[PDB]
Each structure stands twice: as C-alpha cells, then as structure tokens.
Amino acid sequence: AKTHSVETPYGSVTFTVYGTPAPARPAILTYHDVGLNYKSCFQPLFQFEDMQEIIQNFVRVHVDAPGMEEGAPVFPLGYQYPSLDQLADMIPCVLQYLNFSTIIGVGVGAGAYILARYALNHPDTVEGLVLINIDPNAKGWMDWAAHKLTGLTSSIPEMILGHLFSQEELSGNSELIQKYRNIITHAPNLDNIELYWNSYNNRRDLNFERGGDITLRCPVMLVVGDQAPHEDAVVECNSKLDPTQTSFLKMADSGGQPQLTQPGKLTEAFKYFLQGMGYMA
Ligand SMILES: [Ca+2]
C-alpha cells in the first residue's frame, strides 16, 4: 500500500498502488471527479467488502489529479492548470513508472472523460472501461450561457455540487449531501479544485461515431443515475459506441454519485462486466 508521485510535462501527479503483484491481469486504474480525490470519490466503493473480494486478484492504481491529493499545496495565482487532454497525457508516465502495460480504467465525470481520452490515445493498453457520468461532448454555447447565468447567483462550491449531485438531492439535504457540501465548501485546496472545474468545463469533443474510426476498441460499462445531471450525456454516449462491446447501467435511486450511494449494485455490475470481458470474477 504505497503512495507515489511522478513528474510529467504538465507537472507531477500522485497515485496510490494497492494489491499483490498480478502480472496476467490489467491494473485497475481509477480517476476521480471535480471536487473530489480518490478518498472522497472511490474509497467507499473500493473498501466495500464485496469489492475487496473482486479486486484482490488485481493491482489497483488510484490517481489523484494534480493539486487534489491529501496535503496538496495550493497552486500559486495564475497557475495554468492542465486541460483534460493534458491530464490524460500524464497517464503513460504513471504506467511506465510502474512498468504496467494494460489497464481497466474506472472514472467518474471529469475522470471518466480523462480515461476515455487516454483510451483513444493508447487503445492497445486498455482492456476495458467503466465510465460513470461521462459527458463526451464539449460544452455547447447554449449550455455555456446557462452556466454563466447560474454563476451570477451561485458560488463555485454550489456549482461544483450541482455537477456532482442532482438538484433533488441538494434540496433534499441528506447527511451525505451535507457531508460533501462541507467537504468542498471548506476544502483547504478549494482554489485548486476550481482550476480542475475550469478544465472540465473547457474540454473538447471525444467524437465517438458509430461505425466510425474514432471509437473505443474494448468493453465499456457506461453508468449513470436516472434523473441525474449527466443522464442525457451518458444516454447519448451510449448511442455512439459499439453496442456489442458496450453495456449501459442506468440506476434508479442512485442520484449523481452512484459509487457513493449504491456501491453494492455497482460492485455486482463490475463483477458481471469483468465476466463479460473474459475474466473470472
Ligand atoms: Ca491477461
């Protein structure tokens, strides 16, 4: 259980490696959403007992985006934070530092985009992808206008929260919502989070086309909550991928962060995803 760090053209990235050496399986590599880090995004899911049972036969690499890791310094003012594409270009350095040749990528939101871009760049290194809340399209001008309007009366934390959770959830104000409102609003590194939020917002098209030559070439499990902010984007993404290689898990009752609210169902789906990939799980 070791925390590492590597220099890349776009700065250093921190990552934690877990598990016994498993040379004949891909590494499970994770990448978290805006506002979160591995701990606030994925730890509840990966510490879930049923998930522990599956992952014991894999090595796991948990990436913290630059500036998001525990105890990260706040970037100086004017820092040019890497674009999502530049974040995907940090991953070869992580894998070569580790001497790993293939991965199954598991990502949420911004993290799902980053891993999908990584896969497009390096498709022989990616055996499968779990993509939670992916929006593979650039922000359209209509959406930009509505976002800038919203930003006139909402703070950056409130806006990151509307990216993470449904509006029903946030007015519901459950104990998970209050906990995450507090996490983000009072984050010591909130200024770094804003930079990543901006990169998210400012992303380009991934450009999937069904029967196209810009496609993912591995199994993919698309995950989203019914009525959650990214439902439409994930539904649309599904329509652009190879249906024989793609499964779509639209979870009722899960909300904006399925990996936080339904780790049990998500773990069971992962199990069958791996079996469909040809791996005993
Ligand atoms: Ca193998």
Image: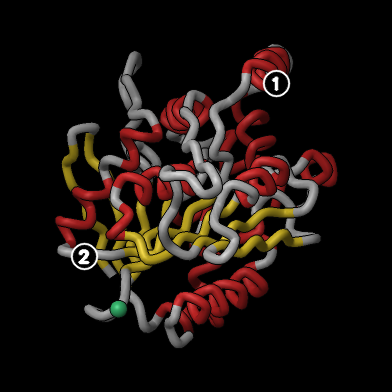
Residue at point 41% right, 30% down? 192
Q: Spatial distance from mark 2 to mark 1, Cα to Cα?
A: 43 Å
Please state which of the two labelled residues, at mark 2 or mark 1, is closer to the viewer: 2
Can the viewer see residue 231?
yes
Of the numbered discs in the image, which one, if any, rests on residue 154?
1
Please tell me which residue lies in front, 137 or 151.
Answer: 137
Total numbered badges shown on the rendered structure: 2
Residue 265 image offset from top left, x and y in percent: 67, 72
Q: Residue furthest bottom?
A: 280
Element type where label 1 sits in the image:
loop
Dividing the picture into quadrants, the one containing residue 3 is bottom left
Label 2 Cα neighbours within 10 Å, binned few <14 / some 14-19 / many ≥20 = some
- Vertical side of 247 occupied by 8: above or below: above
Query: Furthest residue to the front?
Result: 211
- Residue found at x 47% / y 79%: 52
Mark 2 = which residue?
Answer: 100
Q: In x, y percent, where is residue 225?
A: 72, 54
* Residue 26 in the figure: left or right of residue 36: left
The percent position of residue 55, horizontal first and vertical second, equals: 42, 78
Give left or right: position of 249 versus 119.
right
Q: Is mark 1 within 8 Å of ligand 1?
A: no
User: Where is the N terminus found, in terms of image quarters?
Assistant: bottom left
Q: Residue at x 18, y 62 (%)?
A: 98
> Of the residues shown, which amino acid type is indicated by label 2?
Phe
Residue 6, image x and y in percent?
18, 47
Q: Between residues 216 and 199, which one lies in front from this camera angle? A: 216
Residue 37 left/right relative to 273: left
Dot 1 amino acid type: Ser
Identify whether 86 is placed above or below 154: below
User: Residue at horizontal 27%, vertical 48%?
Assistant: 91
